[PDB]
Amino acid sequence: EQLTEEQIAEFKEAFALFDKDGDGTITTKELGTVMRSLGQNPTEAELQDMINEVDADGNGTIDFPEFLSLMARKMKEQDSEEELIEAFKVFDRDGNGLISAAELRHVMTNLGEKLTDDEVDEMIREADIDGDGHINYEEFVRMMVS
Ligand SMILES: [Ca+2]
Ligand SMILES: [Ca+2]
Ligand SMILES: [Ca+2]
Ligand SMILES: [Ca+2]
Ligand SMILES: [Ca+2]
């Protein structure tokens, strides 16, 4: 077990958007066509680095198996990032992108933890990198995964 016929069909449809000429491979040129359509104009060197990250056999192009492997893993990545984003936006009660001590304390009380200002201040100091006494999303992620 691994993938349904419907999952493979949608991966194949995604691959086809890149594989302009239908030869079963994605070249640097084709990847460039797609990004250019999206508003980015990478150089050949930048495109090569992108292919090199996903071209497992080193033949210079990305085939469908290589694209399935990298995509399926990107979607695990994305599912874990979404979980940290949702957790953050809850802590960040006013939506300003900074969890304050007051916000952290309120949400911790709802999570069943009645903490003092000093306790909360220590939690933030542990995670605070830029020294503003607040936790931004990078600081939050960094702490949560490490
Ligand atoms: Ca092609
Ligand atoms: Ca560039
Ligand atoms: Ca390859
Ligand atoms: Ca806030
Ligand atoms: Ca901070």
Image (cartoon, helix red, strand yellow):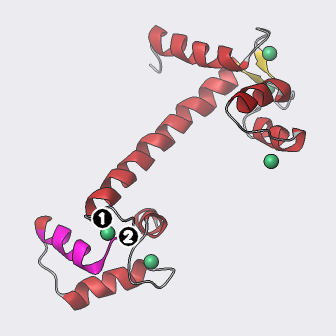
Q: Residue at the location (38% across, 78% down)?
A: 134
Q: Left or right: 83 with respect to 12? A: left
Q: Residue at the location (25% across, 64% down)?
A: 93
For marks 2 and 1 on the same chain, the one whose residue lies earlier in the sequence: 1
Residue position for label 1: 92
Q: Residue 108 colored magenta?
A: yes
The secondary structure type at the circle numbered 2 is: loop
Q: Residue at the location (47% across, 85% down)?
A: 131
Q: Answer whether labels 2 and 1 touch (C-beta < 8 Å).
A: yes
Quadrant in the picture for the N terminus: top left
Q: Is mark 1 within 8 Å of ligand 4?
A: yes
Closer-to-camera residue (101/64): 101
Quadrant of the rendered structure where residue 40 is? top right
Residue position for label 2: 98
Residue type (three-letter) at the residue carrying disc 2: Leu
Q: Left or right: 44 with respect to 99? A: right
| Magenta stretch, overall SS | helix
Q: Position of residue 11 (x, y in %)?
A: 56, 18
Q: Position of residue 78 (x, y in %)?
A: 47, 41
